[PDB]
Image (cartoon, helix red, strand yellow):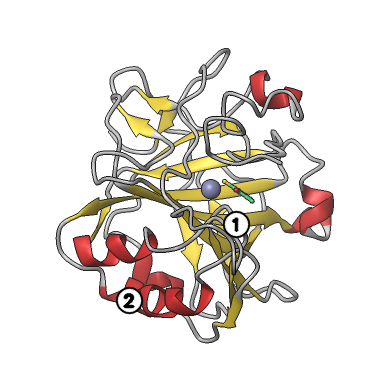
């Protein structure tokens, strides 16, 4: 099945998922000089005070922190979005080395990692119905650079031991996603897709300009995770990022002057 290696990696995905070569694939390179300030964007609103985390899961491609989305509790709205999008999970993509790991790039610059906070449009009732819609999802992307530690990331780093291999999960309640946000909400936005199979073209991407810093010791622990399941030959979970895809018929809008 699909993965990030030579034989089942991004260059292979089109075979099972032909939309891989579609008209609004992600990630993309953000050319900061071609992105246009858009004065028609409303301010962005990230309301995570009632967020309720439940569980953390190694799914063999990354780890997901999953949230209880059965009620109106952690929402994204405003910016390019119409209506209300509810947080369902976050995950990261990262590299084998600090020079690579983000999926989006900014003037061809690769960050050490990228955080994806995934939300579904509440007019569609649930996540499964939302991913059949062109405006079903909104993903808030945040770059990570290696420098100072992020304190609000450490509870996630400390639980990674317990989810080393594919299919392991642990209880992960009362995690506050606010502690993963940079100061500025300046962002670029464009229409795109999931960056993993099934690569559905259902996503409004909101990529923040300001990266958060995490420590080398924090990102080192992400790299100790495994793609394989327990008792299998060890393949470190590293380089689980898809490269930049053709922009095609799309414009990237900036929220800031
Ligand atoms: C599984 C999944 O869902 C939403 C967004 C992304 S990038 C992803 O991998
Ligand atoms: Zn992702």
Q: Nearer the viewer, residue 129 or 223?
A: 223
Task: Say which quadrant the C terminus sits in.
Answer: top left
The residue under the point 48% across, 53% down is 235
Q: Position of residue 144 (x, y in %)?
A: 30, 52
Q: Which residue is mark 2?
A: 154
Q: Position of residue 19 (x, y in %)?
A: 72, 25
Q: Which residue is mark 1?
A: 60
Dot 1 beta carbon under 8 Å from ligand 1: no
At mark 1, the secondary structure is loop
54 to 134, vertically: above or below: below
- The reply to whether the C-beta atoms of the residues labelled 1 and 2 are less than 8 Å apart is no
Image side of residue 18 versus residue 153, left or right? right
Q: Name the disc covering residue 157, or none.
A: none
Task: Say which quadrant the N terminus sits in.
Answer: top right
102 to 235, vertically: above or below: above
Image side of residue 136 versus residue 54, left or right? right
């Amino acid at each position: 099945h699909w993965g990030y290696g030579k034989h089942n990696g991004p260059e292979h995905w089109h075979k099972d998922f032909p939309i891989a070569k579609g008209e609004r694939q992600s990630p993309v390179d953000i050319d900061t000089h071609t992105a246009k300030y858009d004065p028609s964007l409303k301010p962005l609103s990230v309301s995570y005070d009632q967020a309720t985390s439940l569980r953390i899961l190694n799914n063999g491609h990354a780890f997901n922190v999953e949230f209880d989305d059965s009620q109106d509790k952690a929402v994204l709205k405003g910016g390019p979005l119409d209506g209300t999008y509810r947080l369902i999970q976050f995950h990261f993509h990262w590299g084998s080395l600090d020079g690579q790991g983000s999926e989006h790039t900014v003037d061809k610059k690769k960050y050490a990692a990228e955080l994806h906070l995934v939300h579904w449009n509440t007019k569609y009732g649930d996540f499964g119905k939302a991913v059949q819609q062109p405006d079903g999802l909104a993903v808030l992307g945040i770059f990570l650079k290696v420098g100072s530690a992020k304190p609000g990331l450490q509870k996630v780093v400390d639980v990674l031991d317990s989810i080393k291999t594919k299919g392991k999960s642990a209880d992960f309640t009362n995690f506050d996603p606010r502690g993963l946000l940079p100061e500025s909400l300046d962002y670029w936005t464009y229409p795109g897709s999931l960056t993993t199979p099934p690569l559905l073209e259902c996503v409004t991407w909101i990529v923040l300009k300001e990266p958060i810093s995490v420590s080398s010791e924090q990102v080192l622990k992400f790299r100790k995770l495994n793609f394989n399941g327990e008792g299998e030959p060890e393949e470190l979970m590293v380089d689980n990022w898809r490269p930049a895809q053709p922009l095609k018929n799309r414009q990237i809008k900036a929220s800031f002057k």
